[PDB]
Image: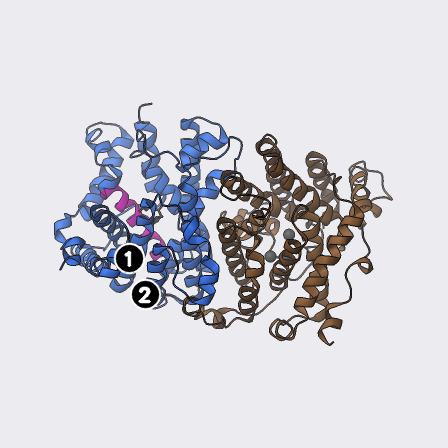
Chain colours: A brown, B blue
Amino acid sequence: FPTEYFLNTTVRLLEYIRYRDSNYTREERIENLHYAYNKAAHHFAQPRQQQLLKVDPKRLQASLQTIVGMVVYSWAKVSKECMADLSIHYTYTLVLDDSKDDPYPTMVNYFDDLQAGREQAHPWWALVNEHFPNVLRHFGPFCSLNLIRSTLDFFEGCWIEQYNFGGFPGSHDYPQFLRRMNGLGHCVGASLWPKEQFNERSLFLEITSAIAQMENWMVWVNDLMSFYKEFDDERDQISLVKNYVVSDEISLHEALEKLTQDTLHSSKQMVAVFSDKDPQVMDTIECFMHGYVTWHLCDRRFRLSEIYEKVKEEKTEDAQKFCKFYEQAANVGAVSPSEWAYPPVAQLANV
Amino acid sequence: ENFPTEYFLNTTVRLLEYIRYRDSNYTREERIENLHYAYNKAAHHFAQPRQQQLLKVDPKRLQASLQTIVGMVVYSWAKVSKECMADLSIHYTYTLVLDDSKDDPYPTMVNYFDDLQAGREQAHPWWALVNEHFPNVLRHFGPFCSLNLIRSTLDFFEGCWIEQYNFGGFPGSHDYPQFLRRMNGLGHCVGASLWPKEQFNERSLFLEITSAIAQMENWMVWVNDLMSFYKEFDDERDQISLVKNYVVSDEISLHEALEKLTQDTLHSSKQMVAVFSDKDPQVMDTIECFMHGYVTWHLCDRRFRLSEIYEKVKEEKTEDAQKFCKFYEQAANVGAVSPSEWAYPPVAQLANV
Ligand SMILES: CC(C)=CCC[N@H+](C)[C@H]1CC=C(C)CC1
Ligand SMILES: [Mg+2]
Ligand SMILES: [Mg+2]
Ligand SMILES: [Mg+2]
């Protein structure tokens, strides 16, 4: 693991994007964290959900928390209810993103069942489509469509990932094709615009553009920050960076530089395009980026903590410019789960 | 200004060499046999009263679209059954027609999801017809492939939706162009429909198929953007194409964007070969037959007026010029077919019967 080269880039992106979540107080975050968590936990604890969603209780609990965090810290300008509902949806998606089961047998009649109104055979679809309306009520038709599509894309993405395939050497189009499939880009980007706060028809071009640009910023920033936790990992192995290596036949270092250039560039352009656009829009966008990074740095899932401390023992300036940031975030978003994530889902389920 | 005839010619010959454009066993009699089968089933379909009244399209554009599509399917899906060509012809005809509705889908998409989950017929007439017909397309494929078709068609709907705004992207929004081309390109639909379950085992060739979907998506749309460039060069009506959006969004010259499209296309082509040459023989055949057919179709269908940019250079001792003409003569040789030989009777005639 190029812990070395790891420092190098993360610092660039952070310094160039200039990570700094100012707006949004700790009391406010906690208030939201608990609202979302609470509604989601009660949801996932219902018997139906409990029996159709096959997940180890502890992974569910962990996933839920990582997601409530992500939504609350990035969808900073939406209502509490919207955060809660988005938290449920993104929790369903994450539970699948880490799973393993062939969907072939349950997808054989997908379309006929869909058109007929019969409950899907794949349990996941049964639960997600049943819950979906609670997510969709927060948006206009256009945005809704994007959510529906991206979630469908995501299902296929997980399907493909089950083959643990990084692409045929020479298949340069494979990597990004896959990252987009399992990235939920359009889902994320469109869910940033609740109809209660934005007029889908008045800001159509703004919203469309944001969906298109955010799709890449969002996934590439995650590929970058995750360049730690995913690796000697099992469900990983097939990451955008690792697929670049396999498919583009280049070194891990070269793929790394690539991701970085795309990321930095994507970042530069997000600003260039939205700075002068509608203020409300620029705020939702800026608040998302800062929150998204805050979440990456704060959530243990990405073990970003180490690469701060364990690089705190060595002055390489590239490992010190990194640390100037981490804390900068942990002091805003570092919150003990005992302050919001309670009681555990399992406890509500057996009640 | 002035069509980059030379640069164009070069790229076109190169594109063809890379894909190994060469003669095949698909005979003219065979094509005609297929052309008529597909056209006939489709025309009878589109001529039914229900279809006739929910699909708002000028009879002549329907007729023209149907023909352009039957041609595209028959000439590119060369290895699939007649029935599959027919059914794909109906589906791709629905898709081509939707770019005729200026009608805002907003009011008809408000309850899209609740109606979908409940099993109630969609409010947008297009969806009502397409989803009703879809099964006839889906029976030809396994679950995985089916899903790709469903998704891409949904993406396509949104693509048309966005295109109604005639928006080429905010200057600086470098991600807009391709984001849009992919949305309205039907890539995954095309790429996945190339593998009928009757002829391919979706599970045995999963990686082959997935990879083809991913690579074909770009080859297919970029080749079309390229061949369609001449017809839309001076066309003041056409305004938001991949190339024109590159200009607006990337803030570069039409010539520079043209370069970008060419490099991606050529490169996409090189890699299609590099990856599939050594793979399963039947897979490489479906792929190769698609590329050659797709190009044949572009050159042969008048929709792209490629005929003109020939009658302008069929006499020049230039290398590219001559190769181009030889490839065109090859195309015509096997693809130039009078509509009176298959496209009959007209849809309108079956409708009023
Ligand atoms: C201009 C036409 C009809 C086809 C060339 C490629 N398209 C961009 C795709 C989308 C629309 C369909 C129906 C098929 C493929
Ligand atoms: Mg994934
Ligand atoms: Mg993952
Ligand atoms: Mg990642």
Q: Where is residue A96 in the image (x, y as percent from the top left)?
A: 60, 64
Circle on res. B136: 2
In the picture provided, is B338 more to the left or to the right than B171?
Answer: left
The residue range painted magenta reads B284-301
Residue B132 picture quarter: bottom left
Q: Where is residue B66 in the image (x, y as percent from the top left)?
A: 24, 51
The span from disc 1 to disc 2 (Cα, nearest Å) is: 9 Å
Q: Which amino acid does label 2 sit on?
A: Asn
Q: Which amino acid does label 1 sit on?
A: Ile
Circle on res. A60: none
Q: Is mark 2 on a helix, strand or loop?
A: helix
Q: State the residue at coordinates (44%, 57%).
A: B151
Q: Position of residue B220 (x, y in %)?
A: 38, 47
Q: Is mark 1 within 8 Å of ligand 1?
A: no
Q: What element carries label 1?
A: helix
Quarter of the render that holds ligand 3: bottom right
Q: Name the residue under label 1.
A: B90
Q: Look at the picture and state if B230 lies above or below A88.
A: above
Position of the C terminus of chain B, as image quadrant, is: bottom left
Q: State the residue at coordinates (49%, 32%).
A: B249
Q: Nearer the viewer, residue A343 or B134?
A: A343
